[PDB]
Image (tube, rainbow over all chains, first blue to last red; front, side, top):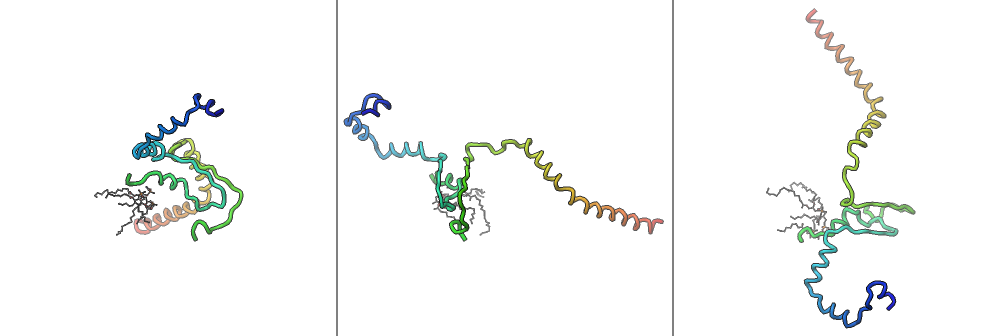
Length: 68
Length: 71
């Protein structure tokens, strides 16, 4: 209750959280994944023992299939 | 002899950065030109003296062959 106020106003009822979820389809998911994941730059953090962890040039080339 | 089996190494860190976030020629003619300088300088005090000698013998030898026939 006390965190909703500082972030939205109008604490959101449970009847509303369910009619948003009635909207999602298979195609809606495909668009919103492409807009945020395809061909973007990541940030990476690691803690030992790591030598295998691949080079940055090879993590960045796994963000696009060379076919689609 | 692959990457997970090469050595053991302790408390050190590295700080990379992306390729699409920066530039390929930061300073092209303000660093490279004074760079070639200190390089060559430091080294053309023991590469030139050997090749002066081959020049001195070369001019002494064609001079002799020429004046032994044409007086």
